[PDB]
Image 1 (cartoon, one colour):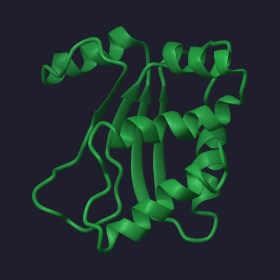
Image 2 (cartoon, helix red, strand yellow):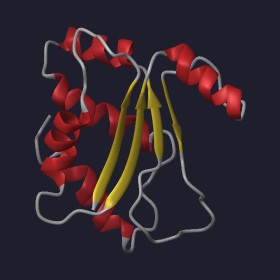
Image 3 (cartoon, one colour):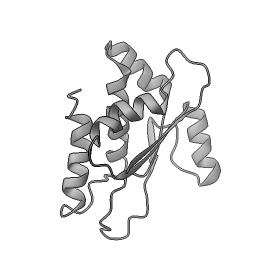
Image 4 (cartoon, helix red, strand yellow):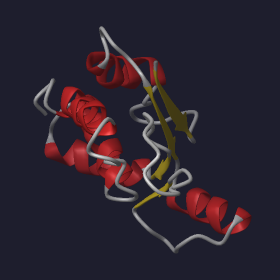
Length: 144
């Protein structure tokens, strides 16, 4: 199925994300009939994520949307999105400033950092239609 990981860092905020809502709304509207994929997403302040990476591997520096891609040997035809790590203060501010439902900002902001970071658009043979339709159903299917 289409499993996604929504890991919030704050317990009390001005607009909690909750996986049920986010996942269901976005990821739920993408595979209402056929589901299959894995998208890990960690939403926490800059310091946490940055330190988190640099503490266990030494990743980049104070970025905006850092994600962790899976093993990219050659082509490997299989549904996947990999791990993701983004800040809420930024996206929440962007979405909050845009004056639009954070629901879309999430599905969009996640995919924005998912591809722009690794490019899960692997092999255009199988993963193509799957991935394409995958991102298309959540991004276009709703028309953010």
